[PDB]
Structure formats: structure tokens, C-alpha cells
Length: 274
Ligand SMILES: Cc1cc(Nc2cc(N3CCN(C)CC3)nc(Sc3ccc(NC(=O)C4CC4)cc3)n2)[nH]n1
Image 1 (cartoon, rainbow, N blue to C red):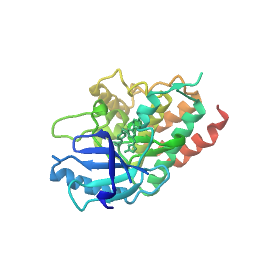
Image 2 (cartoon, rainbow, N blue to C red):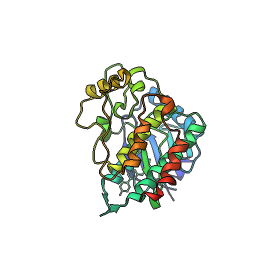
Image 3 (tube, protein in one colour):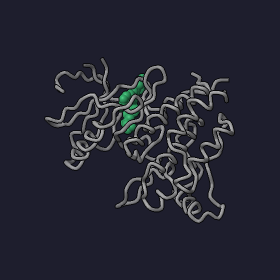
Image 4 (cartoon, protein in one colour):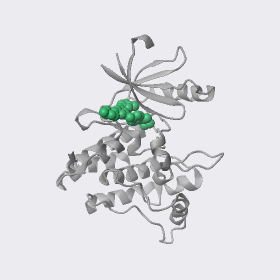
């Protein structure tokens, strides 16, 4: 894509190495690298682009075009009017800017549908959360399949020097203990994400616990002596939906529901629960 065809209007967001801008060509979102981006970051950007080229789904952000011929590299994606899912839900209250319970189901169902698509490709997202989802017009939800280290969500990641930055509060117990990331662990993360949506993003998962306590909690899952703790049922969440969350947090990976079952529950079975 010709970079000259792009007209920059606003800077939406930024990370350690990248910046997202609103651009006119028709609005698109454009991720560009910082002027002080390392060649390491450039290489990561290229890899990121190659991954995105594969993922084509109504509920996955799409790669509309690239500008990699010159520095800094550009990635062009859907512009989503309402920004990220976390910030969107935080600005809303449950219906007595309001959002209804049926809509929350619809939002989660779209996420589930996006993850269902990724599952058929055996693609593991590894960082599913409301902060990595986007909201367009008509409550359209798309999962972001690229990353950016925004300072706003620094507290959502566990940092140790020389280690990978890990979203431990969204990670399955076998993830925390082994670094074992699979589709089954994506399901666990979906459960936490579903919890966020029903909480309307009013609280961080295990928010009153420290990182080390969350890590220790994963050890209690492994041990299985009935001392592990779960995220509590959100006020807006009915028991039946919550039991679904719990199945996502089963100790055994094979006991966690596939995204096909999760989507069916949220899009169909729960329609009678309103
Ligand atoms: C990438 C993308 C971003 C967007 N849309 C938007 C839109 C937006 N604005 C919407 C309009 N109001 C007035 C202000 C906020 N603010 C952000 S702020 C922002 C910046 C980046 C991300 N997402 C990411 O960085 C990827 C890592 C998850 C989310 C929101 N992103 N559409 N497509």
C-alpha cells in the first residue's frame, strides 16, 4: 500500500515500540513503529504482519494492507470506533450509557466465535482479554491478533527480569507452572475474559491478590487438595452462566469446553436466560 495515500489524523495509542494512529484514505487504523525502534522490534513487526495475513474472520481484526518498503513499517487494520473492549465496558453500566445483559452475552458470543475460528487453525492466541478486543459500530467485537505494550495495562502483566512478560491472571494453572500454552489454555483465558465482560471490566481478576499469590494459587490447582480459589460470580451473572465459567477453569485441560460449545451456549442456549 502507498504510504502517501494515508492521511494521519490522530494518535490513538502507543506501546514501547509501536504507535497506533487513526488515518484517512474511509477511516483505517494504522500501527507504525517508533523512530527509535530497534531492529529487533522491526523483525517482530514483520513476523506480526505475516501472522495477521493468515487470520481472516468476522470476529478477528483484519489486515487491510501493509507499508513495509520503508522505515517506519506500517500495518493497516480496521478502525474500530469504540476502541478497546475494556475501556468500552468501563464506560457503561448494567441496565436497570447502559448495556443490557443480553448484549453482554452477544459480546461474549462474538469473542467465542473468533476463538472458534482460531481453534480450527490450531492457532493459540496466548493473550486473550478484554483489553485485546476491539469494539466497532453496532456492538461489533473483533479480537486483536497483534500486540502493543500499552502502559494502561502494565498491571495486567507479571514482570521478572530476564523472563517473559506474562498475563498471569488470565493464564491457566499449567501455563503459570510450565509455560504450556494451548487451545485449552485459551479456553481458560476465555473464562476470565467472560468474567470481565460480566463484571463490565470494573475489576481486575483476583484484584485483591498479589501476583505471587496468584502464582501460588496455580500451585493449589496442581496440588488439587481443594485449596485453590476461583473468580467469584459477577453480580450481573446468573448461576448457569457462571457454571460455564467454571468449566473453563477445570483442572484437566480435556474437561474444558471447546469454543464450539462455548459459542453455542452464549449465542443460543442462554437466550432463554434473559
Ligand atoms: C487498533 C485499533 C484501534 C482502534 N480504535 C480506537 C479508537 C479509539 N478512540 C475511539 C474514539 N474515541 C473518541 C476515543 C478513542 N481509541 C483507540 S485507543 C486504542 C489503541 C490501540 C488498541 N489496541 C491495541 O493496541 C491492540 C493491542 C490490542 C486499542 C485501543 N482505538 N481501532 N483499531
